[PDB]
Amino acid sequence: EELVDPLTTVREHCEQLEKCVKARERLELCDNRVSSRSQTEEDCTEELFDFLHARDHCVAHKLFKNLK
Amino acid sequence: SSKWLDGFRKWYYNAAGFNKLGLMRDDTLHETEDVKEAIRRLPEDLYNDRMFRIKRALDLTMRHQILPKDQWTKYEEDKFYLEPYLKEVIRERKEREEWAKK
Amino acid sequence: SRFLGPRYRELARNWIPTAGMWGTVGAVGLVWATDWRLILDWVPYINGKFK
Amino acid sequence: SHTDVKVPDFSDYRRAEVLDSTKSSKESSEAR
Amino acid sequence: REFGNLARIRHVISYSLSPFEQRAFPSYFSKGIPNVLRRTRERILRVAPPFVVVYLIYTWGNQEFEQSKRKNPAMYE
Amino acid sequence: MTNMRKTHPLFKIINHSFIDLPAPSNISSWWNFGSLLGVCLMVQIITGLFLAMHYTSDTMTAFSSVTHICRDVNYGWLIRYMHANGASMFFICLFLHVGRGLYYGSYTFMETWNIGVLLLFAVMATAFMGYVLPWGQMSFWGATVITNLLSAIPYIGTTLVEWIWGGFSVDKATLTRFFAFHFILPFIIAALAIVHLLFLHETGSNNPTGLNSDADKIPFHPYYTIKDILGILIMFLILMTLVLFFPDMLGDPDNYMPANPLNTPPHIKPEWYFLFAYAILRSIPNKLGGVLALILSILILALMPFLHTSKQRSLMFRPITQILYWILVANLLILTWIGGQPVEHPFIIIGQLASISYFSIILILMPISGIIEDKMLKLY
Amino acid sequence: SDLELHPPSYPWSHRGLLSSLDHTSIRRGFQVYKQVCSSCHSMDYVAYRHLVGVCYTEEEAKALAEEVEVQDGPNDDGEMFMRPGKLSDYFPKPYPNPEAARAANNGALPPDLSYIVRARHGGEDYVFSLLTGYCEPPTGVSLREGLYFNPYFPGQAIGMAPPIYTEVLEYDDGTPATMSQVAKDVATFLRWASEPEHDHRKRMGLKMLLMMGLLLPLTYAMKRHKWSVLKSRKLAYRPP
Amino acid sequence: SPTIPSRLYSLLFRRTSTFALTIAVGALFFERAFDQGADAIYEHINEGKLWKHIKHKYEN
Ligand code: HEC
Ligand code: HEM
Ligand code: HEM
């Protein structure tokens, strides 16, 4: 807890990147869509995968300079 | 009409590429038994001309080059020298096949 | 059309019995080599060995 | 005639050491 | 069949120079680049468009496959 | 004093076959691939000989033996990846060999073409059994796939698959007999290659223009000696960069797991050089129809010399048939790709149309193109 | 679902065509494997004799081989005894048979990590993404206990608990043992275990490119020299 | 006017036996020189990553 993670700093910076901002907007849209309905089989794996692809791509550009 | 067909034949003659090597249609005919009979029935000067044209085409293909556009053979000047000999050989072969069938 | 003609037709007619006998030779050899049940359970003697 | 048979010019392929017709050989053959 | 009696050739003269006396790369670029460009010009129309439509239907098939894996928002009623 | 080179019997056979052979002076780099195939065969023989020197054909010890070759044997990783990438290079050279034969009208050498087709079958069987040999997951499952596809034959298939299996599935006996066959069959390939070269030397060699090359012929040595040496050096460059930098892009990662009968792979595919036949067999929706489509799609190369309806041998002066041939090569690329991805939408219709177009081009469209090409050149 | 999440292309220190591995990173990854990953996974094709020469001194490898106890035998009366390990011994099995591994790991079988990089799509990128990609499941994805949501795992329901976190072990170099650092080190170690011939193969390739960049222009020059007789040959036809 | 290829031909490239001797001696010396140069290039590309670069920390 004392040692901050370079991983999570890069993660939050890539959240601040705007393509991932739009991806999180779709994520909350899917979350409210699924949560405001019972007896449904829809999950938010598609939007989560799109967000994770974009954000992990940003991380893969901009992570390993912080590691030894 | 016939003029459009002649023009399209000219375009195909340019697109075929054997005019760029100085060859002719009878030069580029594949040598089957009837074709070999036609070449053996050819006179001496036409035989020498054909073999020199084939040799020059092989040399140009070896060097991966073509003749200059001045020295390309033209569609109007493409002589059909092997056509009568080939037609006679085909006629004789068809006569032999008909006699063998009957 | 090289093989289509009266001389070739009658040559083929002469060669039907020989080709048919050769086909019979090949068929009998195939049954004997493979020990085919579907044929060999109809001849009298060879029925004995299959029990 | 066979006297009309003349060897064509080869200067587009020939090396620089023997490019001159008036200059003798056997002084650059070892180098080549 | 042997190298001595293959074909009958008359009145043909061949001239060749010594490899030790002529260059191995005689103007390799100046008349080498135009020859390659000429060969490409002669045989580019018969080769390229088939691979172009390979690329087109390759991209179309991958796009259609990914759209098939994409979920369809029509299950609500 | 005598000329020993053309007097000594073995020496005069070597001289008449390889040294003083009258070769066409204008054959391009596409004529290096026969010698490339021979050199690839020798490289495969040597590398597989060392792999079998350090390899055990036991189901329990096949994978551990392969790992022992890769890790413990000195440069055994180099030998194994030389073997695998040489199989990829062997099939590349085979495909370019067949492409040269189709484009430049070399199939008119009918017996040489048929011996080549038999060589192609033998090499495909050799490479299939060799891919089965490391006993990986994809090796075992591809073996089961191919043997069941053979078992699709009515009234013969079940007995033949039990006979080839040595049991009821791919197992100890199947792996051991596949090792024996994979060892022995390249020597049959070599003997058939001597037969191939013997028939070719009987008929002579073919020039790219398709004409009579006897007007201008040169000795094979030193011209094609140094040309084939340059081709061997370039082929070694590609093979060694494939071994030392990209050793797994033509391989399969699922082959690095032990063969589990209980666990299936996610997507089962054969090697990349079986992919067009795999795609057409997936395209025809019948087991007997699929295996017959595979068999006919390889035998149609032997059927090829009876489809020559043109008075020109090579496609050098045949632009319409050139376009059709390049569409055929493009369709083979599509078939390799469709064998790549699994059998889903739209790969169903893409593979079906690819197979139908492939057969239609190679059977119907090319002779019709040759006929109208002769009509356009005013031959009849 | 049926989708797969492709791991991204991370800039490893060995991703270049002439770049070798970071041997200190392989050391830290081996320490991570020994102190964390060895309790469930097996590495039966890698030994301490493989470790010596690229990561550890012979004495250090002997010490960390003798710190574990291995089963050996038989002795004179025929009884399986236990002895300290040696260099030639391989890494010890945490389970004697895969069925015991399935019993002790809630049905899931932990695969052998001697070829996992060469046997998974992506390799070390996949290993890094799987180890650092643990996240809460989204809405509508109900996962029973014993399974954890992981987007990079095919099927998205892995049977692996999150094995590494911040300060999960102590490094001997003083390197901060964060999640990303531990994952990168263990991915480098797993890449080495999958391809022990990595740096040697890269050196072979460098020598091959230098050698072939020497040979190919010169061999081409020899070919053009021999073929210069024909490529400059002139033909004349003189009929009478 | 005698150049370096001229001296090389007049001394070593004339006879086949001394040609082969030149090839063998050049093979020995070029094997050593090429191995040294390619190894040094590899070390300079991978400074600070190899075991021969990091063994001094963990030895003695
Ligand atoms: C016991 C709690 C384990 C620890 C410690 C480690 N792993 Fe593991 N792993 C474990 C199980 C039970 C499984 C099977 C899960 C499944 O659903 O199959 C795994 C699997 C893996 C895999 C394979 C993933 C795949 O898609 O095949 C990998 C690559 C993996 N584990 C990596 C890994 C590493 C690097 C570890 C050390 C940090 C590690 N695991 C520890 C059980 C356990
Ligand atoms: C192990 C397999 C093979 C070997 C060792 C082999 C060997 C050779 C060699 C050395 C040549 C002469 C060099 C050349 O023309 O490229 C040649 C040419 C030829 N090959 Fe093959 N070949 C093999 C497979 C095939 C296949 C698969 C085919 C066709 C389907 C084939 C058909 C031909 C033909 C027709 C020629 C003559 C080409 C010409 O005359 O120009 N061969 N082969
Ligand atoms: C005398 C000749 C040959 C012998 C003795 C031989 C032997 C072997 C052995 C022992 C293996 C197991 C090693 C391994 O799995 O990597 C193997 C694998 C293999 N063989 Fe051969 N082989 C020969 C020729 C060939 C030929 C001619 C081909 C293809 C044209 C071929 C293709 C393969 C392939 C693809 C593998 C799989 C390699 C892998 O998956 O890593 N082999 N062979």
Image (cartoon, rainbow, N blue to C red):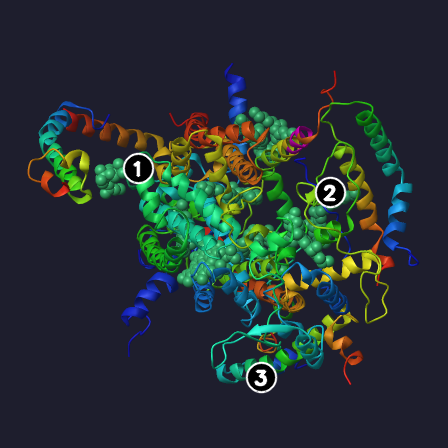
- Label 1 resides on the chain identified as B
The spot of residue G2 in percent (x, y) is: 65, 35
Subunit of label 2 = G
**Circle 3 sits on which residue?**
H25
What range of the chain is rendered magenta? E62-68
Tag 3 and tag 1 share a subunit? no
Q: Quarter of the image containing the N terminus of chain G?
A: top right
Q: Residue furthest right?
A: A2
Above or below, comparing residue G37 to residue F329 in the picture: below
- Mark 1 is surrounded, within 10 Å at the Cα level, by few (under 14), some (14 to 19) or many (20 or more) other residues, namely many
Q: Which residue is mark 2?
A: G151
Circle 1: element type: helix
Residue denoted by label 1? B38
Q: Position of residue F183 (x, y in %)?
A: 39, 60
On the question of residue D6 being in view, the answer is no
Residue at mark 3 to residue at mark 1: CA–CA distance: 62 Å
Residue F294 appears in view: yes
Q: Amino acid at mark 1?
A: Ala
Dot 3: element: helix
Q: Is residue F302 above or below residue G220?
A: above
